[PDB]
Image (tube, rainbow over all chains, first blue to last red; front, top):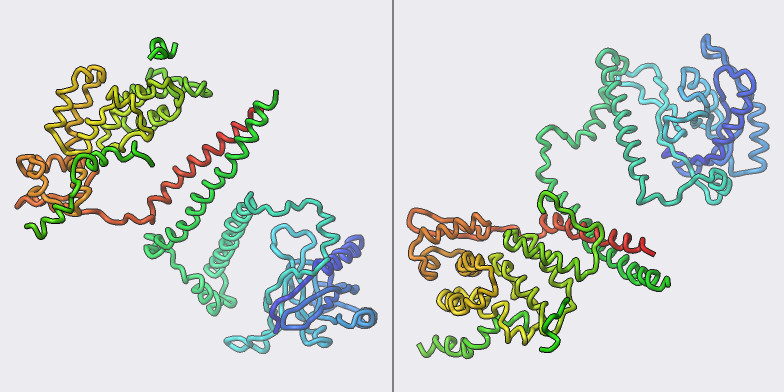
Length: 286
Length: 40
Length: 229
């Protein structure tokens, strides 16, 4: 395999309304329903999906039920009314996974050989995009365990469609179009500096988890390696960027030229009609 | 205030100081000093 | 004034604010604050264009440009020649000619010859560093011309009688930051040189906060000007 996904918010509301279907009744654990999908390339798409009744008792996390007859009858309806659509996986509303999810996944990989799950949150405040993709494949193990069948975080994104926001941006009414030039950059400053480096501080919290704990899979495979991709910049004290300040002066050069010349011409913009219309409105007032 | 007696009774203003040296001196400047190479 | 300086909230009639900045800039003439005086006396010069055809703008320019001659360098003054000025010989055409020449005999012939009109100057502190402005105009012209110059050339070509007197003038020139000269005090070498990095790497992009601070000031003066009707 999967490149990434294309997921419209329509199917997310198709999770939300069934969360309304279960929020009125006894919610045991969470929602598990079908994720239909439009798989064409190694990229993915989802235009629609549906749900299915489900309970689970947490004693061996193996007593859990869908209705495959209901799944294939309503899938026969939706396949009948739309030949484009097919199943691509499932979803769950509780944002943390558990051990049964490989039995859900591998139990429904019999219909199509991939069955991607979707993490969402019905009350999201801290995540970025809600949508999430795994794939249940193996890297065996370095020790080669008996089939360490593993979910893999395939990258994920919100999909888009022409004329799908006809509802949406009319509904929300709150959008300030083109806040370039005012405070959007510092919204992204607070949220990327703070909300980026706090994630860095939870990764260094996981480093302390390797200090006092974390011997499970101490993970000396990807961590220092892509952290050496990070360590393309060893930015230690004395800072060692003598070969970057004439670079910085080259970067500052043209832009401060544009501010000098161009903003002098911005003065040349305001002054003419400001004076002429000024004294028109001044000495032509009486 | 202003009068009290007086109602009864890139240009040259840029150049006139060097043009003074173009007014009294060095008329045939490198044409006698230009002639120093062969007259002397 | 200096303990209780209070100037206008808003400027008055431009004749009054013009002549007012001429008065206080004419105080900074004798106070010898040469930086502010050239721009407030330039401002005051250009800001009063209306005058009687026999003068008072040549009075304002005449008694304006004396310390501008005393800056060590001057441009060739204004830009609009006046013949009744030429009859009155007010701001000394011949003396500023003696300034841009490195001359001393005709210079002090202007000084000694016209002293009844130097009474009409009333600012005899002009000459006491204006002969010094002749010699600094000479060393500034020659030093500005040559890449390297030596005391064997200038110290007796300008007849300063000795190496060390020119080393004192270049001591005051490096003290004034005029020249990037050096002097080997062993054989008598002014081992003078010219510094480098005239490119627009850093200095104009630093200057653009003065250029654009100026521009935003005129933006806001245009806005406050718009606030009136």
